[PDB]
Picture 1 (cartoon, chains in turn green, orange):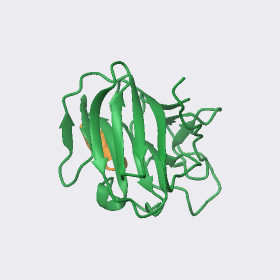
Picture 2 (picture 1 turned 135 degrees about the vertical axis):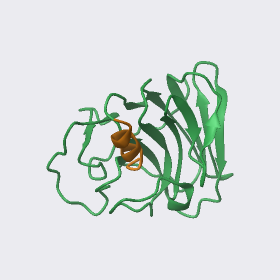
Picture 3 (picture 1 turned 30 degrees about the vertical axis):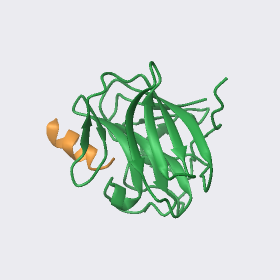
Picture 4 (picture 1 turned 90 degrees about the vertical axis):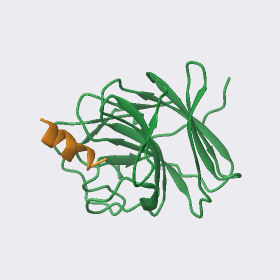
Amino acid sequence: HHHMVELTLDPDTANPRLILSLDLKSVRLGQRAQDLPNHPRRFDTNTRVLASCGFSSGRHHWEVEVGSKDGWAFGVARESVRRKGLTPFTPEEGVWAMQLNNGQYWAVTSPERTQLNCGHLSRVRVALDLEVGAVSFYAVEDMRHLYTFRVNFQERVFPLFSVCSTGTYLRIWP
Amino acid sequence: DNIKRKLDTYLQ
């Protein structure tokens, strides 16, 4: 029994175009925006949602089931990640993520992304280590390493999820 | 439409 943190998507953060599953574990992009209460924590233009739980210390694992189609990115964000207006999806903006775009897997480095030659992903294990300052990604099938960002995190870190195209999704386990 | 697809990924 691998001990993973119990995460729920934070509806107060979700872009209004996102459709969250009724268990708040899954996210996809809808065809149209919902009328949601204006909230300071809400991503009003970028297609993002955070978990309701953030981390200041220790080691935390969770898993993300990923769609086969382009349009998703996920990882962690610093709490101060900007919510309002169009923002860059980059480490400078406090986003540390992997992405599926044009049939290829990427670590979202800046100013150019880093192609991962990892083969098809069904489910990814995220290993957040706030003792050492790292976030690592593994393919669950054989636990092959995908990517590690090494960050001297200076604030609370939140699980981050983005879906910018219809026809794909992300789902938190457990 | 690649225009919407490129414009889509700017919203990530």
